[PDB]
Amino acid sequence: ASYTVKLITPDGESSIECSDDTYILDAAEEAGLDLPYSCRAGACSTCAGKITAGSVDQSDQSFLDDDQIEAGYVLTCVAYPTSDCTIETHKEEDLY
């Protein structure tokens, strides 16, 4: 399955295709976007984004708390799309 991922960045929106077995950060990088990351392992907030439509599988995430997850926050470095989705990027600074 190929999903359309609309990335809402501080500098503009860009829609990319992302396979069901590709992490959203990896898809973004292949498409030529420059999204933030550090550990690439689900254990920080550098790569945080926020889902505003659709769904992901981020079962390997181990930084976000349940309230953050229920608000739509996602660790892009470990999140596979499970539908077409819309994700706001560069959201680390919105976390508290």
Image: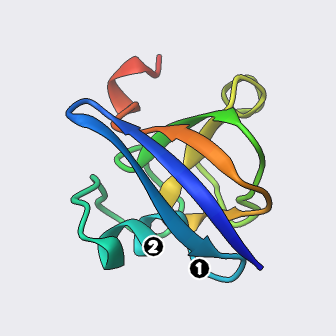
For label 2, the crowd category at 10 Å Cα-Cα, with few meaning under 14, some 14 to 19 and many 20 or more, is: many
Q: How is the image coloured?
A: rainbow
Disc 1 is placed on an element classified as loop
Mark 1, Cα crowd under 10 Å, few <14 / some 14-19 / many 20+, is: some
Structural distance between the alpha carbons of marks 2 and 1: 6 Å
15 versus 27 height, above or below: above
Residue positioned 71% across, 35% down in the render: 53
x and y percentages locating residue 48 in the rendered image: 45, 42
Disc 2 target residue: 27
Q: What is the x, y in percent for residue 55?
A: 78, 48
Disc 2 residue type? Ala
Percent across and percent down for residue 24 are 52, 64
Q: Please name the residue shown 27% across and 35% down the image.
A: 12
In the depicted view, which residue is nearer to us: 69 or 51? Answer: 51
Q: Which mark is residue 69?
A: none
Circle 1 residue: 22
Q: Name the residue nearer the viewer: 74 or 13.
A: 13
What amino acid does circle 1 point to?
Thr
**Residue at the location (40% across, 31% down)?**
91
> Is residue 84 shown left or right of residue 92?
right
Q: In the rendered view, would you say 72 is above or below 95? A: below
Image position of 85 (left or right of 49):
right
Answer above or below: position of 89 versus 78: above
Quarter of the rendering containing residue 58: bottom right
Mark 2 and mark 1 lie on one chain; the one further toward the N terminus is 1
Cβ–Cβ under 8 Å for marks 2 and 1 = yes
Q: Position of residue 75 (x, y in %)?
A: 54, 51
Instruction: Give the mark count.
Output: 2
* Element carrying mark 2: helix
User: What residue is drawn where x is 54% and y is 69%?
Assistant: 17
Looking at the rendering, in which quadrant would you find the N terminus?
A: bottom right
